[PDB]
Length: 171
Length: 61
Ligand SMILES: CCCCCCCCCCCC(=O)OC[C@H](COP(=O)(O)OCC[N+](C)(C)C)OC(=O)CCCCCCCCCCC
Ligand SMILES: CCCCCCCCCCCC(=O)OC[C@H](COP(=O)(O)OCC[N+](C)(C)C)OC(=O)CCCCCCCCCCC
Image 1 (cartoon, rainbow over the protein chains, first blue to last red):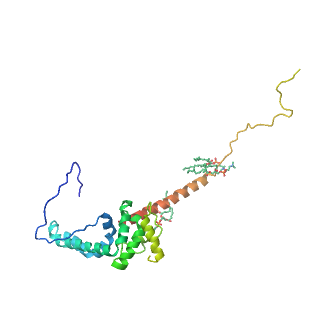
Image 2 (cartoon, each protein chain N blue to C red):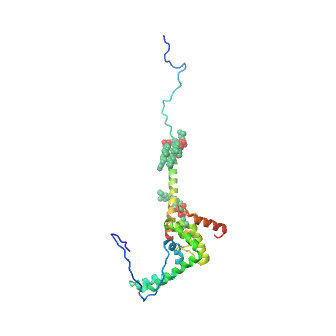
Image 3 (cartoon, rainbow over the protein chains, first blue to last red):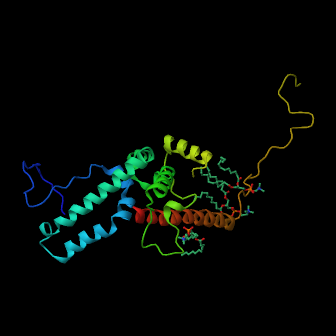
């Protein structure tokens, strides 16, 4: 919760899970693919994530050990979403997070690639990108036309793919 | 007799300018104040619009 100062030295641990708890395979996506598919991880895995944090609230202070069985399932369902999005939308998911690794991982600067990614994932994986807590009479930010905050330079691959999706009639 | 001196012209020189030539230039001051308030208000329009967008972007992230 506080960060290490004044000569911290890092250390790691040559050990294993005990036999009591089964194997769980991990998430291997880094920040730009994780930030790219964050809304679709949240759209599919909402009741699993909320049961995990509700576990953590319910049995206070035990925490780690009494919530492992649902921390299993949140990781497995997010892995399901990520390979689902790989095998359907690999090239434009890659287009999106390759836009996102420039521009400080700001979602504000990658609108023309995220329109393509949202259209693919919505027609093929049937998951929708939504911002909750947003009452009506309020436009969502990634839908608006001519925003005030444009990026410095639009990425070339995504504006080329965006124009070709215009002329195909994809989007 | 007088031969070979510097003398003035037959009709004299034409008059030079010895008055103060300080013409009042510029617009009225209320024109400058109205332009100042218009520029500043348009800048506040764009600035407060951009702050509200940046807040909606923060909601997204
Ligand atoms: C880089 C950003 C900063 C820009 C500077 C600040 C904005 C300008 C505000 C003051 C000027 C103004 O607009 O004043 C406008 C007034 C108009 O007066 P008039 O109607 O002709 O008076 C009539 C009075 N008689 C009857 C006696 C004639 O004066 C002028 O035209 C004088 C010339 C101003 C030149 C501008 C200076 C810069 C030179 C480079 C050209 C761009
Ligand atoms: C104490 C001085 C009071 C001055 C009052 C002036 C009345 C002007 C009302 C115009 C309303 C408007 O047009 O505002 C619109 C703008 C932009 O809004 P938007 O993002 O497009 O709206 C989005 C709404 N959604 C989210 C529902 C979609 O918003 C502003 O903030 C700018 C106000 C205009 C300039 C105000 C200048 C104040 C400068 C004060 C320095 C002393």
